[PDB]
């Protein structure tokens, strides 16, 4: 018999992004080919199968720095981190291959699906 | 607010 | 020129609630008249003007335990904590006064608004 | 996915 507030999840995510932009309560640095990205472990886990696995590991859950595979492109990661905190994906002809490869590595199934569809349309 |  | 994934914010919140239910990466205990509630500081801040003010304070941001005013009802808090993580509010004739009072104290404006409207309809 |  609950009532539901339609905009609540969006408003929560908007506030989480405001905290990220002001570097409030960020608890991890993600290192991508020397580029550094500060974030909240819980948001990373909520969006990515890879971060979910990393931060549920009894040893890795305590790390303040995570280094990604050197093949990962920092721009592709940046676009995906922005998507995690906003639901908006900056998908462009010039970045689609790097975004899809990063989303496959991060295990972000819905992003991989839209990249596959956008690539299929251009062939 | 809605009835979900 | 971004594309947007409609269900992303809801899916993020659903995963944050799964982490809460499994007590994963919870970093604070909220004490309400001896009852204890584990949660994520970032989610509390994203939903409540009171928690936002508390955890942006340079001393309180580091506390692992927060004690609420003794007038706060634990059931009212529990219903509001559930709403924070789900967008669903269990509003009933028997709890509406305690829920509104707790939402006013926590500074959850949209919850206060619906409680005022539901109370006005019964008079 | 939509055009926001
Ligand atoms: C599976 S239970 C669960 N519970 C809590 C969290 Cl934080 C979580 N995250 C997560 C796991 C896998 C995947 C994603 C998020 C996005 C994606 O495409 N795959 N999962
Ligand atoms: C105002 S900027 C901002 N930035 C980040 C966060 Cl985490 C935040 N939360 C917050 C503040 C006030 C209120 C709520 C959340 C719910 C409500 O009714 N009032 N606010
Ligand atoms: Cl470390
Ligand atoms: Cl995704
Ligand atoms: Cl403490
Ligand atoms: Cl609210």
Image: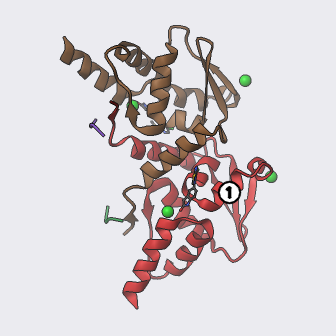
Chain colours: A red, B purple, C brown, D green
Residue C8 position in % (x across, y down): 44, 55
Residue drawn at point x = 47 percent, y = 22 percent: C106
Camera-side residue: C111 or C93?
Answer: C93
Residue lying at the far bottom in this picture: please name it: A123
**Quarter of the rendered image showing ligand 6:** top left
Residue lying at the far front in this picture: please name it: A1
Label 1 environment density (alpha carbons within 10 Å; few <14, some 14–19, many ≥20): few
Residue drawn at point x = 56 percent, y = 52 percent: A46
Q: What chain letter is assigned to the residue under label 1? A: A
Residue A91 position in % (x across, y down): 44, 73
- From this view, report whether residue C104 is shown above or below residue A55: above
| The residue at label 1 has a CB less than 8 Å from ligand 1 | yes
Image quadrant in which the C terminus of chain C is located? top left
Specify whether A110 is left or right of A43: left
- From this view, report whether residue C76 is shown above or below residue C16: above
Camera-side residue: C11 or A122?
Answer: C11
**In this figure, which residue is indicated by the disc labeled 1?**
A53
Which image quarter: residue C34?
top right
Q: Is mark 1 on a helix, strand or loop?
A: helix
Residue A6 seen in this snapshot: yes
Residue A76 seen in this snapshot: no
Camera-side residue: A120 or A92?
Answer: A120
Residue drawn at point x = 25 percent, y = 21 percent: C118
């Amino acid at each position: 018999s609950c009532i539901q507030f339609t905009r609540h999840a969006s408003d929560v995510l908007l506030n989480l992004n405001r905290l990220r932009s002001r570097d409030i309560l960020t608890d991890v640095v993600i290192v991508v080919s020397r580029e550094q990205f500060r974030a909240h472990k819980t948001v990373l886990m909520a969006c990515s199968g890879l971060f979910y696995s990393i931060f549920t590991d009894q040893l890795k859950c305590n790390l303040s720095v995570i280094n990604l595979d050197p093949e990962i492109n920092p721009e592709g990661f940046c676009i995906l981190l922005d998507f995690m905190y906003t639901s908006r994906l900056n998908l462009r002809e010039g970045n689609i291959m790097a975004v899809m490869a990063t989303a496959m590595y991060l295990q972000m199934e819905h992003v991989v699906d839209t990249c596959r569809k956008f690539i299929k349309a251009s062939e | 607010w809605v009835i979900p």
